[PDB]
Length: 282
Length: 282
Ligand SMILES: *C/C=C(C)/C=C/C=C(C)/C=C/C1=C(C)CCCC1(C)C
Ligand SMILES: *C/C=C(C)/C=C/C=C(C)/C=C/C1=C(C)CCCC1(C)C
Image 1 (cartoon, rainbow over the protein chains, first blue to last red):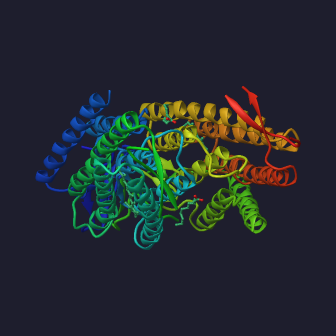
Image 2: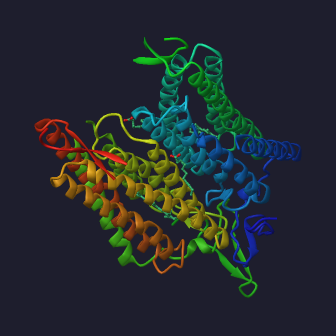
Image 3: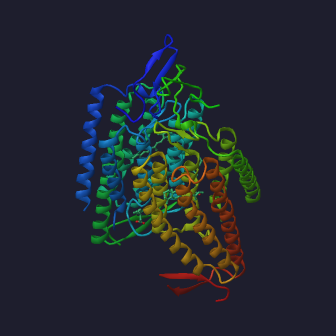
């Protein structure tokens, strides 16, 4: 049922595998089960829900918050890819060391993670701003994925080496992200904007923290999850980190724009680093 | 000589391949030659030259031009990886569709390409600046690599689909890079700073243009190059785009710092978008 050799014969008391000389690659490890059909159905359900969310968001989404459009476009594009080839090469990489590495997921990360951190870097959406710290957020994060991908393709020790490399990059990514949220909390007005900024932080760290968690629980780690079981949990934290988080960031930037129009753009320097807090009256 | 099955037997008039049931994966396509030993030696030579350059640059390199340090660190780190596992999994991905995808290269791109575009975004190295356009440079470029990687792992039509996807992203990356160089040329002083800025542009577009060129010439494309023969040319444009280009960017930012100290930071608005040209006298 795949584009590689799946039918074979055992010979010489199980010490020889004979396969057809059809030109297809063959490995016994690739034929291990991805999981239970109860988990496959659970994954195929959330695939539509996330796809429906992405479509509802692209509908709903139609300053210019281009960041939300990009991850949503990439998301529902990926689900079109996923519906038709959720386990075909190269959506799933069946490598020479028997590793099934879900490159579809890690590619979607590389496409959307820096765009979320860009949205985080300009949480208020105000003007051509950002900072030098933004580059630290984007350079470190791409690192974690590249190491995390490399770890998933690798096996044994070097998987740990590259996972620990990606973990160290991930620690740098989380801290600089806290420095962004901390300032963003004290920059946005005292109203509901600070409620949604704090909530965006929780959605951020929780969902983002689960990615190295699911890497340890999944086949990439000690395999306490199935390949289907890893697709389920990943979809949940994908939904949290991408579609719901971009929604609040949209709801935040709306509350900012209204406040900026009604009360104007008013700044009151507050000490922490000096932040220009948005206020109501001059 | 690899971590996958390399010894096998033909049976039934060449219609059956029998392999040992040792648990190793097996594919006939993975056993195709990478190239000629004359080309392997040529690749192993430039590997040291690039490694020696990276070491000489890390020596030499020791505002804070952190960007040059990063690609140089990643480069000589990669050569340590390359010297020991230039064709082991997952430095080279032997996938179920017989594709050998050199993930070491594409990972090094993901690690260093956005850092070069960051250096390009702050060519003068002056202050916490950058722009919104920078995000277009970084989002588009990561796209080209992700599609280009996906194309290299893929086969046939979808390789073209993802290559054309990466090509469209690459066109966006090159244009916004020209807009950066064009402004950088008119921002830096009239002296030798404009010579080195123009030269950085030529090193940029030539070496960067060769990457989709070598993708078409290599096994990823019509295979007019060998796998070793692709390692040779890639090293050359790696050397150009990374070590030599970062050197000029260092020589540029030095000429800027001296000019800023001697003549001060003087701006004269010139029309193109309005650029604050660095001048000598007020
Ligand atoms: C939409 C998906 C997002 C925003 C995913 C973010 C994922 C990470 C930050 C993953 C990090 C990992 C580490 C820091 C350790 C190495 C393995 C991990 C990659 C999965
Ligand atoms: C140090 C290496 C660098 C800076 C490499 C840059 C490589 C590219 C911009 C490659 C681009 C490609 C396309 C635009 C078409 C798809 C395939 C390519 C990836 C290799």
